[PDB]
Amino acid sequence: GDVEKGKKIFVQKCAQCHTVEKGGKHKTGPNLHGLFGRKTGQAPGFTYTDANKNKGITWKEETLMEYLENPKKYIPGTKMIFAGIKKKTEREDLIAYLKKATNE
Amino acid sequence: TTPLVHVASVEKGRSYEDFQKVYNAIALKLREDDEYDNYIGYGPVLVRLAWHISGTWDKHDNTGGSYGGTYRFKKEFNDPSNAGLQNGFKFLEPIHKEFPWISSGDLFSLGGVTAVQEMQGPKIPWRCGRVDTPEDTTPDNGRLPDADKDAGYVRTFFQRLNMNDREVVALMGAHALGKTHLKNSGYEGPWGAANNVFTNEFYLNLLNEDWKLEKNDANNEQWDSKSGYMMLPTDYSLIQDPKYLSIVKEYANDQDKFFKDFSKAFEKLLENGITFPKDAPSPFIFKTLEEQGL
Ligand code: HEM
Ligand code: HEM
View 1 (spheres, each protein chain N blue to C red):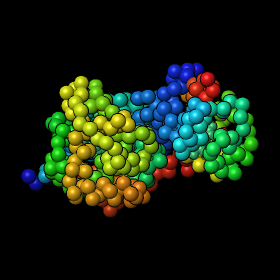
View 2 (cartoon, rainbow over the protein chains, first blue to last red; view 1 turned 90 degrees about the vertical axis):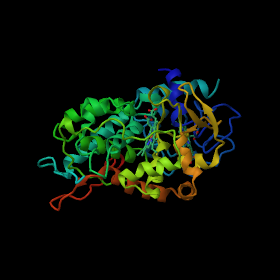
View 3 (cartoon, protein in one colour; view 1 turned 135 degrees about the vertical axis):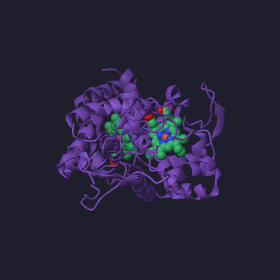
View 4 (cartoon, rainbow over the protein chains, first blue to last red; view 1 turned 180 degrees about the horizontal axis):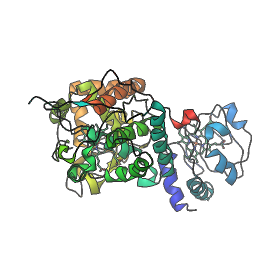
């Protein structure tokens, strides 16, 4: 839906751990630029977990739509301590905002 | 004088199995309705109705408290001290309608247990048995604290509810949650960064930021960090006193302790004034959604 509303989502549940702009320092989490159309454990400079890089998948709309329900579920033994968003609307609203924010 | 007694009484034929359902219902909505107050969700406000209902107790005469669940009546309900809480009440209601047999009081306090546990916080034992009391049991507005005072006032405030310094400091760490609203309390700003996740950030924010005293559009003064957090005058006392200070550092350092002290004090908070028989069930430890894989 919105990037508008999607924006709020991000500040609130994730910005505590990630930058979205290229040259966004990595804090407890990688920079999220270069997301849509990229693989796991992809961010150059981050101390990923085998488990991550190795999920070996493209970071795409629906892919997120899944992930966002259950980060743990979708990828065993990781460091991202987030319990996923469970709804679809707001998972959808965050996914929008991202396409923007994570590239241009 | 010589007080009133309130004895718990299980909602006729209710089991531990009925309770988890009341619990779940709330946990599930908490997840439905997470849009409220910018994606904060209703958790925080629930940790705070819990307290506002409980916080009217007076160990002198054993009046107020969580038992009679009088918040459901216009005097308490409209106490200016309760401004904000009507949001958490309307969130509770439909639930109250699905489970008509629960006391307002158990609803209210369970409300707070649910939220804590669902925000990655510590398990909290709970006891059913609060019974709804007649409208004439609602204490007068004004047994709740002000946010403009000192360590002094804060130590003394908690003595009317048999709370000691270790216990008031531990409850105060609940400020990691939510935020203040200029429109309800005359304060604006969160206490930290994850305000819907249960942790000890309060204490580190206290200890590490550059508090600066500034005055607001409500014309109250409040400490402001340039990190975009605030600290009420009274949250500031915890560091302006060596006793409270000693504890802040202790919890700033070890969360598993902080957490251990909170379940204890929180439930003590929820239990003042209630007489729990023999022919009474022990505190329940409800299962979070995450453990029922819901
Ligand atoms: C809520 C919104 C969030 C979004 C959309 C998000 C997105 C992501 C994505 C897509 C990845 C995988 C990167 C890749 O392989 O290309 C990731 C990893 C990670 N995120 Fe998040 N994240 C969010 C919240 C959080 C939060 C709240 C934290 C708190 C610490 C966090 C910390 C991390 C960590 C530590 C990793 C790395 C896991 C590993 O490689 O071991 N994220 N995040
Ligand atoms: C020292 C005594 C206390 C004072 C003076 C105080 C004062 C306040 C004020 C003025 C607000 C903001 C009202 C609003 O703007 O909505 C607030 C929010 C809150 N209080 Fe405290 N409080 C105290 C004790 C407690 C205790 C004992 C707890 C928990 C058990 C607690 C939990 C909270 C929470 C979670 C919030 C956030 C509310 C929201 O986000 O809607 N507070 N408090």
